[PDB]
Image: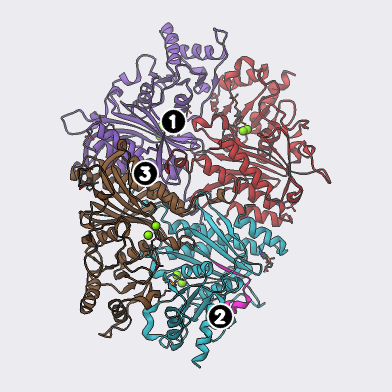
Chain colours: A purple, B red, C cyan, D brown
Amino acid sequence: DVNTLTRFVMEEGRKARGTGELTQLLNSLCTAVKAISSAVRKAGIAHLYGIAGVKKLDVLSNDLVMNMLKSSFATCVLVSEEDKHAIIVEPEKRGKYVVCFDPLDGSSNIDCLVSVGTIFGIYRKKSTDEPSEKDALQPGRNLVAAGYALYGSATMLVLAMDCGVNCFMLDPAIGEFILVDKDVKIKKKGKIYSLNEGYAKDFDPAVTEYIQRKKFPPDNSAPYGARYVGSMVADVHRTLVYGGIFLYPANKKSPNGKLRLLYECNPMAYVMEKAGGMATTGKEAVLDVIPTDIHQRAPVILGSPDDVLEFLKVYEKHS
Amino acid sequence: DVNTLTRFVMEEGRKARGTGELTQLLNSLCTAVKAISSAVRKAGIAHLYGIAGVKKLDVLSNDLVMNMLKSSFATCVLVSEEDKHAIIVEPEKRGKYVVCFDPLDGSSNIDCLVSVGTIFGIYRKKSTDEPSEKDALQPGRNLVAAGYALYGSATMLVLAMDCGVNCFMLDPAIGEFILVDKDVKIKKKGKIYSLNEGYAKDFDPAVTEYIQRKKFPPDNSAPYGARYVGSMVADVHRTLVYGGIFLYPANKKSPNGKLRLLYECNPMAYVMEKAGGMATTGKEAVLDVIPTDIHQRAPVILGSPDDVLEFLKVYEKHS
Amino acid sequence: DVNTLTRFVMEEGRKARGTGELTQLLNSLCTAVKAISSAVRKAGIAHLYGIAGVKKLDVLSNDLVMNMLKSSFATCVLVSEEDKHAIIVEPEKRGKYVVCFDPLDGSSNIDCLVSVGTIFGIYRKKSTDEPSEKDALQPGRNLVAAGYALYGSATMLVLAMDCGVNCFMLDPAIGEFILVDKDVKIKKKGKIYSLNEGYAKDFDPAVTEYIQRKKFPPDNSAPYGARYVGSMVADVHRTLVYGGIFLYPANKKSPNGKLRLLYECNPMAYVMEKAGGMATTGKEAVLDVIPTDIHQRAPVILGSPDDVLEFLKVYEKHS
Amino acid sequence: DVNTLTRFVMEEGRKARGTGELTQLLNSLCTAVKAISSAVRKAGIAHLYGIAGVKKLDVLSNDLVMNMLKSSFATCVLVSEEDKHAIIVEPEKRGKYVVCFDPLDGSSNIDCLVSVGTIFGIYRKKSTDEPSEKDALQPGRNLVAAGYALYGSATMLVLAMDCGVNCFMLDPAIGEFILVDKDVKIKKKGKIYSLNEGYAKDFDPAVTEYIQRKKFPPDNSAPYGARYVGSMVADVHRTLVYGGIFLYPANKKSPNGKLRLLYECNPMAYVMEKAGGMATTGKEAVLDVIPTDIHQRAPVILGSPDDVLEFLKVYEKHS
Ligand SMILES: Nc1ncnc2c1ncn2[C@@H]1O[C@H](COP(=O)(O)O)[C@@H](O)[C@H]1O
Ligand SMILES: Nc1ncnc2c1ncn2[C@@H]1O[C@H](COP(=O)(O)O)[C@@H](O)[C@H]1O
Ligand SMILES: Nc1ncnc2c1ncn2[C@@H]1O[C@H](COP(=O)(O)O)[C@@H](O)[C@H]1O
Ligand SMILES: Nc1ncnc2c1ncn2[C@@H]1O[C@H](COP(=O)(O)O)[C@@H](O)[C@H]1O
Ligand SMILES: O=P(O)(O)OC[C@H]1O[C@](O)(COP(=O)(O)O)[C@@H](O)[C@@H]1O
Ligand SMILES: O=P(O)(O)OC[C@H]1O[C@](O)(COP(=O)(O)O)[C@@H](O)[C@@H]1O
Ligand SMILES: O=P(O)(O)OC[C@H]1O[C@](O)(COP(=O)(O)O)[C@@H](O)[C@@H]1O
Ligand SMILES: O=P(O)(O)OC[C@H]1O[C@](O)(COP(=O)(O)O)[C@@H](O)[C@@H]1O
Ligand SMILES: [Mg+2]
Ligand SMILES: [Mg+2]
Ligand SMILES: [Mg+2]
Ligand SMILES: [Mg+2]
Ligand SMILES: [Mg+2]
Ligand SMILES: [Mg+2]
Ligand SMILES: [Mg+2]
Ligand SMILES: [Mg+2]
């Protein structure tokens, strides 16, 4: 029988004997995702082109998530890609939770109408101190909930908590996220590798050899296919649904990768581990990295466990 | 001054001194595209999941186009990816046009929600009385119009005719395509290359060398960036919008290429040429291939003229 | 065969051998109506209530019809209830048609969410001097097309021409008006009467007597049911679809009624007659009044011919 | 700050320190209302008219409320205009609440696109017996919550509880009910009376005299205006919003009134009293009537307190 995100999250809160504060936070996030979706699909674009005779989506998306998270009364510290410093919620609206998000991921793909998305990770504040930026410098092991919305051919919200990974399709006729994939697990091994090979000149030798194994298998088998949308949400989601591997490794220029630990790599690493996949920087599990800067980058290699393991094997040889 | 697709096409038809039959065909196709977009964005999916207590998308898309074109009274021969032979329109609903289309391109990977699209090409028939599939076996240079709808982060219709290429954004709030880019032209030279490098082991020596020049430039310029969504409409539309080059060349599993000439390669070659770009098979312009089978494949290299020229210099070396 | 409003107007124009100007006018009206429908249904209301941390509907509606008609290149004079003088279209955008319209009928009614609508009538300019207000002072008999959009439980457009009356339902999933009632004809006699009985103290004695025959039928048949939405478009649409009588009659406090001749009475009077109905002031056919003010009022009694004739019999008796 | 129905209801639930069962109940109802709204506005009607080559709205709406309420796990007994006997939820899905509802109200107005609605009343099961139709025969006084959805020019949900009455506007761009009117109170005295005067021949003398005081005021102030949409939800909501009085008194076809006590009269009476208005049968307060039949009928007079009292004075004089 049918299940909605609103009802699924409410029942989970009841099972967990929560006070309803994280439930209100998720409710507010789901609302914001729906309004971002509506804007990404360009509803109302006709009023921008004179049909009756204004703000970039990056900014609007951030404002939507910021205001909805603030007005939830569930959050104290908010970290966003769009903000230099962490936002400390005024004390009247303060709750226990720390949220790191990317309100619109995939900026290079906005103008060509390729898939984009929203990423989020949720922490419970651990300090006794006044809430500050330091409450967001937790390792991803500490995540309480994380996931993303994909604004692709359809809009899907993927939500991961300790109970597992669940996928919800947004039905736009009724503005309702519908549970369509329950307790999702990733394939043990896939057949697609995903990275920007235009950086090949700057590749670490382990990355160079790994990719070469994908195109010219030593085990006679057939070569992997290649995909790279250029939007982390789209590429990571395909990895979940299809299996395979995704890599934004440290290249000569970016010696710590490009993607941001708090609101891109950690949320995706958490979805992956909860789905029976893996997420490594090469040196360690992504969720084991202890950050020191809220905007700090990390290298990320993630996906099916047989694939990540094969990469790590190559990486160990080279180190 | 605001303009819609319905009004734009109608005025261009008045300037053309058309009898209205092609305009009626194009209205019908755009209605179909709006209904494909709705299904693709998963409107009503809550009913499939039991909200009140099943046709595949590409089958439903085909039915939408087939029915809207037949009932336009403008067509006589219809070629689709999903039908073995050409559909001859029943006599009472016959007009003069031939339409070759892919109703849902990239549809095999719809399961991961990556962008998807509809591609179409329109010809005037050559036959005089009974139409046949011979009316579809024309070279792309005979196209009267061609285009595509992209179901991406937003839905956009790109329409090309002799007058040039125009882009329309679907405003879902009112179901109108809004003219947002008129008389579009690709940039002379781009910075993105797009192909499935997973087939590298099977590349012709010309493709191997060209891709090598993009990753390790001879003149030590910046290497190109790589993008491969895996859906032709998405990869081609980005090529139109951002410039660069898109390749689906011959490999082992596909020695004449994989993409279909009539309703994948030819309509995109036409869009590209009308925007000042190029589309080649390597040996000849795509639009000059004379087809002998409605489902025949063709290699395709397309995009910015400087990039396609640079590929063709490498190709002529290996003749 | 499925038919859309666009395709139906377009084929009607080709059958009438029109040059495309009227078709372009109606296309523009269609687009404006879908945009009004969207604002009436409160799309985007969440932004006015600060979800991301402003025209009134009658004003927005007027701007939409005004802008879409001007940019149609099909009109020279535009009369609106929201503007004191006729609007003269700038010479570069001038067509040959005169449009009188009420952009959002049902004022008493917006705040309580009851049905509202748009009424329009279209004349061809008869004079050969430069477009002026006098070009709109034509009797309804000269109408080339008229009709209305109803924003009710669903949105529907009713379009009347010489060919007859047709009804189109707006499907909001795809933003297409769908032909659902062709060549509509009104019942010869209804069972509903529609007027504001709160004015009973001021009624013309004929209206008093006529309403008494509907509550106390002298043949001892069933009394009529009463319905008075208070929104002309809703009450007259129901009159059209169910049969019956709608009255906004002259009393002595308002010897010309309340409703406006040019953009309320004449359009519904024309829709009625083309459906086999009637529409009278009590003294003459509404469509036969020669207006002298673009805002002059007219009494109306309209609906099923048996009912209207029943009323005129009572009216003649009081003379 | 912006507030949604999902967030308001959850916050009121946390305050009352509920277990979340009632909150799940209202969530499911909210989702059903949205899906009914989408069907009422004829989303997807194009597919019913053959765009690609079914129930009455009554049945579908019932199936939507019925299935959503069952799957909430919050209910044990369900009573609906569309079902002869009370439905007893299977024990695995049983909660403690009893819900009586009209899933689509205003049946005579469906076909002419006039406003229609949904009405609901929520009781807690008092008896500790096996759940039965008996558990629904409580007087309105015992109502935990009630309200209605109006599918008018826009869709609005009106929800009443001990805490008061609140109004939520459906934003269809995002499928979210947005709090727009808080703690609503009706005017002390209105200027509109609402009833079907078609039954004038059957009215009792109290009703006849009250209506005569509204058309011919003894104090010689201005007569009230008349409005009768013919859908109870629409007329009752205009009564809440503008003030005045709504009447469905006994007539010859309906000697105990037409409107039904459990799922029409009691919810609207409850909303009225929580807003500072009144609702009587003429003999008692609606909320005081102890029902013996789940489909039993009652006459009803409701609106601004002064108007209901002025009618009651007339009713008292006629004794
Ligand atoms: N909707 C929920 N779904 C899953 N787990 C929840 C939920 N709500 C609360 N929890 C768990 O219970 C803890 C306390 O909840 P709270 O009282 O809302 O802060 C959370 O940090 C989660 O570990
Ligand atoms: N809307 C239109 N826009 C641009 N060219 C058109 C249009 N309609 C017709 N034409 C041109 O006129 C030819 C004949 O039109 P038709 O009479 O409708 O078949 C077409 O094949 C086009 O070359
Ligand atoms: N779509 C149409 N439907 C019905 N009649 C039309 C249509 N278009 C034009 N006509 C008729 O033809 C006349 C001239 O059309 P036009 O050349 O567009 O101004 C109009 O005034 C109408 O009488
Ligand atoms: N969202 C809510 N809003 C207002 N009151 C509520 C709410 N939820 C529960 N209550 C009150 O608390 C009682 C018990 O709640 P529950 O355990 O959900 O059945 C209800 O019957 C109401 O009186
Ligand atoms: O062009 P590149 O260097 O391959 O970068 C693509 C990656 O950058 C990103 O776009 C970074 O996110 P932003 O768009 O927010 O800057 C990722 O989504 C994506 O994986
Ligand atoms: O997986 P590959 O071998 O790279 O092929 C991808 C190409 O095939 C296609 O998916 C063909 O489209 P369809 O299969 O949907 O007809 C193109 O969209 C795409 O360019
Ligand atoms: O309240 P009244 O006097 O009975 O008048 C109602 C009539 O006035 C109108 O509201 C006039 O239209 P406007 O709202 O544009 O003034 C009609 O819709 C309606 O039939
Ligand atoms: O035609 P009448 O007798 O005035 O009936 C009107 C009343 O009947 C109803 O339609 C009865 O409700 P249903 O339409 O669900 O049967 C009420 O909505 C309305 O107030
Ligand atoms: Mg970003
Ligand atoms: Mg990002
Ligand atoms: Mg294809
Ligand atoms: Mg295809
Ligand atoms: Mg008005
Ligand atoms: Mg008006
Ligand atoms: Mg009812
Ligand atoms: Mg009913």
**Residue B171 numbered mark, or none:** none
Residue A75 appears in view = no
- What separation in Å lies between label 2 and label 3 (alpha carbons)? 51 Å
Residue A19 is one of the magenta-drawn residues: no
Of discs 2 and 3, which sits in the foreground?
A: 3
Left or right side of A117 for C119: right
Residue B237 place in picture, x, y as percent: 58, 37
Q: Residue furthest top?
A: A317
B96 shown above or below A127: below
Q: Secondary structure at mark 3?
A: helix
Cβ of mark 1 under 8 Å from ligand 5: the answer is: yes
Image quadrant assignment for residue C147: bottom right
Q: What numbered label is drawn on residue C286?
A: 2
Amino acid type shown at disc 1: Val
* Extent of the magenta region: C132-147
Question: Which corner quadrant of the image does residue A255 belong to?
Answer: top left
- Left or right of D229 on screen, residue B148: right
Q: Name the residue nearer the viewer: C217 or A18.
A: C217
- Looking at the image, the residue that sits furthest to the right is B128
Q: Say which residue label 3 marks.
A: D68
Q: Nearer the viewer, mark 1 or mark 2?
A: 2
